[PDB]
Every structure is written in C-alpha cells, then in structure tokens.
Length: 330
Image 1 (cartoon, rainbow, N blue to C red):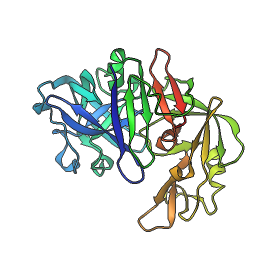
Image 2 (spheres, helix red, strand yellow; image 1 turned 90 degrees about the vertical axis):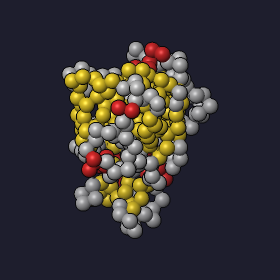
Image 3 (cartoon, helix red, strand yellow; image 1 turned 180 degrees about the vertical axis):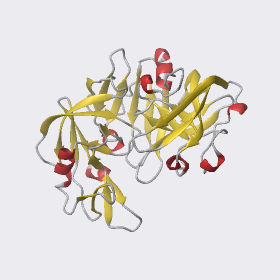
C-alpha cells in the first residue's frame, strides 16, 4: 500500500504545516501537524477542557463506531518550545492520503497548553519520530508510520514541504518526479529516538564551504533551523545590521536587508536554502526589525534541521531495519 497527502502552511510565514487525517467511522477529518521530532498522535477532542478549545476541529470518540478506549492508558508530552498536552487514549482507524491503519492509538487531549489553544488551525499532532519516544503509559504505543510499515510497498515516508506553498507527505513510495538530480542518503542514529544525522558542513551565501560535522535532527515539527552558535554567528555577520537580541529571543535583522542563502552538506551533496526562506518577518506588526530563520541551538541541547532547512529539499525518511535519511534538491 501507499498514501499521499497534501500538506499546507498554516500562515503566511510557514510557521507550521497541516495535513488532513481521517479518524474513526464515519471519518472525522482533522488537520494535524506532522512532526518527525515526536511520536505521539494526539488530537483536540470532545474531552478537551472547554476553555482550552478555540476554533479547532475536535475528535469525538463516541461518534465513531470503531473507537475503543485503551483502558488505563494515559499520555503527557512536553515539546522543545515549552508547550504541552495530556489526556487518555483510544484506538481507532486512521487514514492518511488513502493509507489506512486500524487499531491506531489516538491520544485524546484533556488538557492543552495556551500555545495550542491559540492556534486554531492545528487540531493535533501526528508524530513520525521513533516509537521509543511515545509517551503513552503504562503501555507504550506505536506511531502511525510504525503501524503502517509492514503494509507499505517500501518502508519509507517522504517530506516535500513548500515555501509559501502546499507540499506533500508520501508513505510507502518515492516520487521520482518530485526532485531534481539524485537523492543522497546519510546515516541515522535512533539512540535519542529522533531522525538524527550528521551534516558534513555549511556555506554562507557564495562563500566557501566549511567542512565540519554538525549533528542534528530532521524535525518537520520545528519551524526554524537551529545550529551551533559559531555557525549562526558566521551567517548573520553577512547581514548588515543583524544582531542577537535577548529581548526578542534571537537574531533579528533589518527588514530592508536582502538575506544570503545558506548551504548545508549531506555527504558530498549540498542543499541550498534561499535567503528568502530565512525571513520570518517583522517581530511585531509594523516593525522594521525582522526575525531570522536561522537561530542558535545553544541551550537547546541539540541542533535542529527544522522546516527552514527541510523545505529546501525532498527528504526521504527510510524506516528500513537500519534507518537512513535521504536528501535531494528540488
């Protein structure tokens, strides 16, 4: 089997992407944030504290003939941005882009933190990291991909995120019309539960490529690109007036600037992030200070190849016995 679903930016800045997911019988369609940096599929639901729902589409298990309470199971998750959610668990039928998993753990939110409430466009998250990170207790549950894997034509999914435009998540096949040149594959460590890999270096604009190993995670659920402070300083030093602001919480730059591109290494291959991808607009409405799309990972504890990086590529998440990541230009 295979599946293919369109993923759509939630706003003009590509702060995140939502993908429609069918849950239950009859189908309840929710727009979920596919997150290769976590491993819980959780949704706004009929059980979510009323004051914490503001515009989201909710899953109502009692209206699904295939929903079953996973007795005793609870979940609770906290993300790198400080947001969180928690609740109980049903199993139900979940389909993505024509691909159906029966018996999927659907984690029903009783509580969500303010960040989720305030984002009316995201009805929940669908985790695609490794199932070892799943938070369901006392019986850990599998991700959608993990459950689908054996049935898939090939044990892979691909992320093809758009810049200011829709893209595609495919399951079980590689669309060879969706990228240019070749796909360069690189080793993955699953030791932290993430799609963790080592970039071979970087370049700023038309500058020379610096060979240096940068360990990081491929994370569709993080907006920006988070790299070591040395690397980020080297980038913003090429932008007149750019500075790191503790008050804002990162590098800002004059909105009048033309940003240089950023290149990262995948083995001997190179992925180029156009400068425009790194512009996340005024820090506040009407400001002439703009927020940078490349930020320091110092004090995150890990480097993160978020959407800024991934949307410049066609990315293969290979869930073979020995997992790997593949990157192609597009």
